[PDB]
Amino acid sequence: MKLSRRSFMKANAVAAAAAAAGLSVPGVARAVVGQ
Amino acid sequence: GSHMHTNWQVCSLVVQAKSERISDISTQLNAFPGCEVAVSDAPSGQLIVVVEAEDSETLIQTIESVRNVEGVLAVSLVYHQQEEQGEETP
C-alpha cells in the first residue's frame, strides 16, 4: 500500500487529540531529551 | 526524506463510541480509502481517524456516518493536516 505519513501525522494528531480529547500522551510527555 | 510534501485536504477526527463499538465501526474507517484510523487507543472507547476528500464539504460528509452510528455517542474532530502554508492553530 502507499502509506508514508501516518507516522509523522500521528505525532501531531495525538498532540491535538490528547490535550483535547483527553486521549493518550504519546509525544506529549517523553521530553527528557532535547537537542 | 529530501523535499517531498503535497496534500489536498485531510484532518484527524476523534470518533467516540462504546469501547467495543468503535472496534467495529472505528476499525471500518481504516478500511475506507479517504477515512483512515491514525491512532487506535481505548482510553474511553474513542479512536482517532483521519479522512480526506475533494474539500471540507466532502470531509464533513464522512462524519455523518460516525455521528449517525449508534455505537458513536460523541465526536471530537479538531486537527488540520495539509501541506501548503501555515496560518491556523493546533
Image (cartoon, coloured by chain):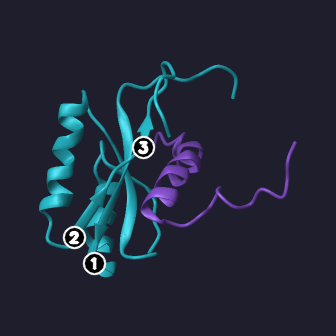
Chain colours: A purple, B cyan
Secondary structure state at the residue bearing disc 1: loop
Occupied quadrant, residue B42: bottom left
Q: Earlier in the sequence, mark 3 or mark 1?
A: 1
Q: Are marks 2 and 1 on the same chain?
A: yes
Residue B37 appears at what percent x and percent y?
40, 56
Residue B82, numbered label: none
Callout 3: residue from which chain? B
Q: Is residue B33 left or right of residue A19?
A: left
Check whether the beta carbons of the residues at disc 2 and disc 1 lie within 8 A of each other. Answer: yes
Amino acid type at circle 1 is Lys
Label 1: chain?
Answer: B
Residue labelled with disc 1: B18
CA–CA distance in space, label 2 to label 3: 20 Å
Mark 3 or mark 2, which is nearer the start of the sequence? 2
Which disc number belongs to residue B73?
2
Residue B67 x/y as whole percent: 17, 59
Question: Mark 3 and mark 1: span between their CA atoms?
Answer: 22 Å
Give the vertical position of B47 relative to A33 (above or below). Answer: below
Q: Secondary structure at mark 2?
A: strand
Residue at horizontal 59 percent and vertical 22 percent from the top: B4
Estimate the x, y position of residue A1 in percent, counting from the top left: 45, 44
Residue on which disc 3 sits: B79
Q: Which amino acid, mark 2?
A: Leu
Considering depth in this image, is A28 or A6 the residue closer to the camera? A28
Discs 2 and 3 carry the same chain letter: yes
The tag earlier along the polypeptide, 2 or 1, is 1
